[PDB]
Image (cartoon, coloured by chain):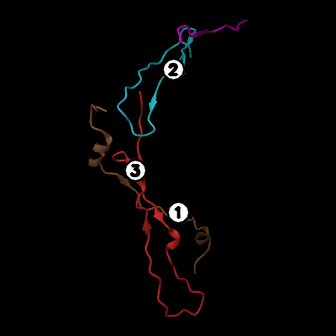
Chain colours: A brown, B red, C cyan
């Protein structure tokens, strides 16, 4: 169509995306390592 | 907070392909496994949507 | 407390007639809705009653 202003696709080329550190799905709370005493 | 309206979630692919070695007893001089952690090449990206009037 | 014995409770009428726009994806340049909040023209009024002897 006949756009009246700048679009989002063209405008986002000037913007920084927020990036997370990689997420690991195999992480568990590991309660046993906290319940035990270490000598 | 999202600084510019785009949020990218990076994820590890194939977590089962990271190889570790654990000895049960009488350790030997065998070579250790070599591995790395792989990432997804097309992570999901979230862009904020508007509610307005 | 009631300063002069009359208490008026004002209420909103037709709360479902307030129109909002929410986008699911790929926002466009369409016109936004125009709305307002309406009030009841005959609110209920409470006047204090006496218990005396």
- Say which mark, if any, is on residue B7: 3
Residue at 58% in and 72% down:
A33
Q: Which of A2/A36 is in front?
A: A2
Can you tell which quarter of the image residue A31 is in?
Answer: bottom right
Label 1 to label 2: alpha-carbon separation: 45 Å
Q: Are marks 1 and 2 on the same chain?
A: no
Q: Are marks 3 and 2 on the same chain?
A: no
Name the residue at 43% across, 68% down: B38
Query: Which of the 4 image quadrants contains residue C28?
Result: top left
Relative to A10, C3 lies left or right: right
Q: Are marks 3 and 2 in contact (CB under 8 Å)?
A: no
Q: Secondary structure at mark 3?
A: strand
- What residue does disc 1 label? A25
Chain ID of residue with mark 3: B
Q: Nearer the viewer, residue C9 or B5?
A: B5
In the rendered image, residue B53, in percent from the top left (x then y), is placed at 41, 27
C50 is within the stretch colored magenta: yes
How crowded pointer 2 is (Cα within 10 Å; few <14, some 14-19, many 20+) is rated as few
Mark seen at residue C44 = none
Q: Which residues are magenta?
A: C40-53
- Is C45 one of the magenta-colored residues? yes
Asked if labels 1 and 3 touch by Cβ distance under 8 angstroms, the answer is no
């Amino acid at each position: 169509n006949e756009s009246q202003a700048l679009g989002d696709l063209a405008a986002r080329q000037l913007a920084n995306a927020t990036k997370t550190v990689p997420q690991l799905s195999t992480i568990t709370p590991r309660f046993l390592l906290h319940l035990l005493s270490w000598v | 907070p999202v600084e510019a309206g785009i949020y990218r979630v990076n994820r590890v692919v194939n977590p089962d392909r990271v190889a570790i070695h654990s000895e049960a007893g009488a350790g030997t001089e065998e070579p250790l496994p070599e591995t790395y952690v792989d990432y997804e090449t097309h992570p999901r990206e979230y862009t904020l949507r508007s509610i307005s009037t």
